[PDB]
Image (cartoon, coloured by chain):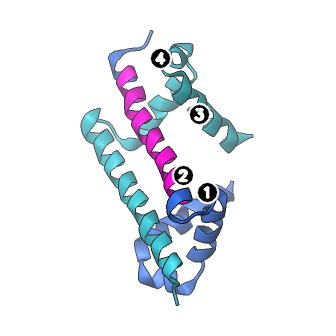
Chain colours: A cyan, B blue
Amino acid sequence: GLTRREHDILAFERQWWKFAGVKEEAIKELFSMSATRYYQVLNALVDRPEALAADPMLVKRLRRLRASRQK
Amino acid sequence: GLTRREHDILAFERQWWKFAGVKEEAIKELFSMSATRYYQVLNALVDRPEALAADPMLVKRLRRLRASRQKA
């Protein structure tokens, strides 16, 4: 039943899912922490003005993603 | 005012944020469709019975990621 393009979308999408699988591992091995605690730290850090100075483009978009899940 | 771990966390996060950008561009060049219409097709496709059968874990995470994105 799956069309060719439906087959290709799923296969393409899955590759981004296996990326999520490496990031979890990379967090565990790079900083020696759970993925959950990593995002708790990222949460707190994003609102610090010092983080904004460091990478202005990145934390502006992290802030926008934050504000769209609540508002 | 940033510690070493905090600067590294932000650099590490920058790489994955750059990945999401490349995914959008890949959506537009490969499938020649806008990102929003891609997720329309993708999300309508999860409800299709043959998609659940062909791959259990992908749609199950995709089903579980929109259910959570909706419940609150």
The structure residue drawn at horizontal position 52% and vertical position 84%, both measured from the top left corner, is A3
* Dot 2: element: helix
Residue B39 shown in magenta: no
Specify which label sits upstream in the sequence, 2 or 1: 2
Point out residue B50 in the picture as x, y percentages from the top left corner.
51, 86
- Dot 1 and dot 3 residues touching (CB under 8 Å): no
Q: Nearer the observer, disc 2 or disc 4?
A: 2
* Dot 3: element: helix
Q: Nearer the viewer, residue B71 or B4?
A: B4
Mark 1 — residue?
B35
Point out residue B47 in the picture as x, y percentages from the top left corner.
60, 78
Q: How many marks?
A: 4
The structure residue drawn at horizontal position 35% and vertical position 47%, both measured from the top left corner, is A24
Q: Are marks 4 and 1 on the same chain?
A: no
**What are the residue bounds of the magenta stretch?**
B7-27
Majority secondary structure in the magenta region: helix
Give the answer, above or below, for where A7 lies relative to A44: below
Q: What's the residue type where badge 1 is placed?
A: Ala
In space, the residues marked 2 and 4 are separated at their CA atoms by 25 Å
In space, the residues marked 2 and 1 are separated at their CA atoms by 6 Å
